[PDB]
Length: 492
Image (tube, rainbow, N blue to C red; front, side, top):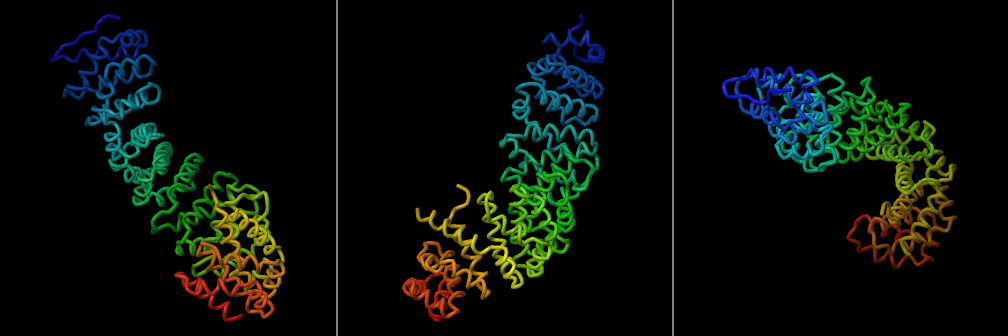
């Protein structure tokens, strides 16, 4: 435990320091002392001889294995030095630098702030165009460590072009450890409102889709979690066919986290996207989602997104009618009505009411929905929800609008109209005409319009004093409201 000096024009000093760092005995003596540790750093940070830099970086690396060696480099200002070396043209130096930084980030307290201040994030993002996978795996892990729970770092990663670079890695490499660490960076970034659209624009959804049948469960699951974050209100994408097919297959997985994510992504991607609705139906998505709901039982983390996806798939696309029938044909009607009952919570009830509204568009579903008891439960929901509004999550006004809307469609059928009227709903429907909410006025006037095609019901509506509020509604700025109001008035 002796030498501690050195001088300009000589680097045989470093070439002797290094070997001592291999032997733990001498290694503890050199790191217990803040003497030449600082004198190691200056060398590395300054010289233009390539072999001294790697000898210097190599030494710092060997010291990073011990709690005090980390402290040594840290207190000695090794972090800005190490970050500077991330610009080195020697692969061996780059590798020592990122690895030492990695060790500091893992164990040394204060290292993360120190790396951020030193401009580490920008340098690490810039290194994502390198081609060595073990190097990329360390680099992306440093980024995960620095980005997690740190919004500031996330925005810097975005500004530096992180999303495209990470997406390119997922589209390029097969090395599992690298794909997994890169997916964890994307997962962290995917909850940032700025990073999310950037990742989508980079083609991140399609890229993550590539890995959904990888043998590595941790890789699949991270891709799924990230996809669920990204898919929520994304721009319309091309080349989604493969991803959509795989998600439908994943619904049948024995892993509940896989099923939950698959349903949620399918829900997100099908919302108002008729192209995606079509593709999903074409690969048997209705059957798969119904099976998923049936198997899920009272697990609302699965049923809620699955029912939302079914709601999307049963509306407003070329095969919507086929889908409406398919829910019935795959034995789905009884469970859908069941989900309107306790123990279902409000989000699930809201989604289920919406699905039933779409299913009722299909005449062949009118009788089975009635037989399964959809009508009285929808009425009870509506009555209680209306009372609640008149006295954060789901607003009861949404349940009022939803149930009335479902009853509006079910009322196309003559037997359903008899049941609906038989439940003393006309007085409530008329009171809903007075609602502040145009959407509620609309379905209320709509259901009254269906009911009023039968003479006996037309008289009951008139007797309920509907004429006055309907006349007010003739002048509604909402053309749908005005049209239904005019139609009820006519039938009376």
